[PDB]
Amino acid sequence: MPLDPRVEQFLAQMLSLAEARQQFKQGALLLDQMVPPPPVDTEDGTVVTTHGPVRIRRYIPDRLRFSHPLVFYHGGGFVFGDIDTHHGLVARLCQTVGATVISVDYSLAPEAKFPVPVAECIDVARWAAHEAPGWGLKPSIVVAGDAAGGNLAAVVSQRAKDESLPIAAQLLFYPALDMVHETPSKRDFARGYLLEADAMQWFGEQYLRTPDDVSHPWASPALSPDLTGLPPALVITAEYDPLRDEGEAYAEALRAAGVPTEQIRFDGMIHGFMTMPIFPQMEAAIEAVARFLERID
Ligand SMILES: CCCC[C@@H](CC)COC(=O)c1ccccc1C(=O)OC[C@@H](CC)CCCC
Image (cartoon, rainbow, N blue to C red; front, side, top):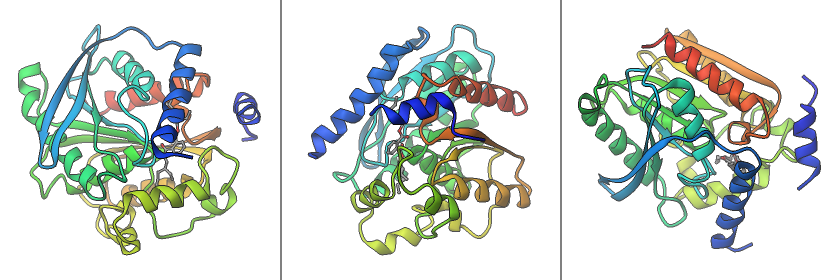
């Protein structure tokens, strides 16, 4: 419950759009150098979405143990990140679960704005549902994402029924869910825990079209008043993350809507930890993912 010691060390030791994207990529590949991912067979590809081609990467496990494709949406505040920044997480998800994983390079803001990545993420999920029989898998997919990518996975899940899209589960890793309400964790951990109040504002300015967008349910899936019938859900939070309370409240709300829900707070942890392989909690959370999906298919 105190701040993990390795996290403390991490936090102690630490301007242009293109080069802000760059330092994000460099921070990521620096973590991967320090703690290399397992080897995994991949193949690049493209998906035709209603907003353009979107690059994807398919991960193939050494040993296929799971009978649904995972579709992973990377985080980074809708502004940063890509297939490469999240390779360390996706590689381990692929090998630990023994699932084929579709990692998605959706359109980043501010070039694309809300709700372009929502539509594209829906299109890729539909693509994967269509391909699944030909991979030898069940047609129902698992959607998954971290932070901003958890937001997308949550919106995709809520829109699944309307869009005739089969989803077997949703893995939300410290997701952003509510852009309207100021929770206690948002106030208590506003500064100093990697993800900051000022950054969250800036991401919002880049992603949304106008301030009114914050209350739209495809920006804020938490405001959706009827969560009955949604995909079984694994919701992971970090204790010391401003996003913690919305994530946890959402899992509570799903539980009360009859949705089979597993809720896990990682104590001592901060936002982003599932892409930070310097922390052993990253692999623990990946084992949590593998255990949860055993209870699915
Ligand atoms: C090896 C991979 C490198 C990246 C890794 C750190 C080394 C993880 O970083 C993060 O998770 C992260 C860090 C800073 C800013 C944003 C994020 C992020 O994903 O979500 C931002 C949230 C803001 C609330 C979107 C909500 C918009 C209202």
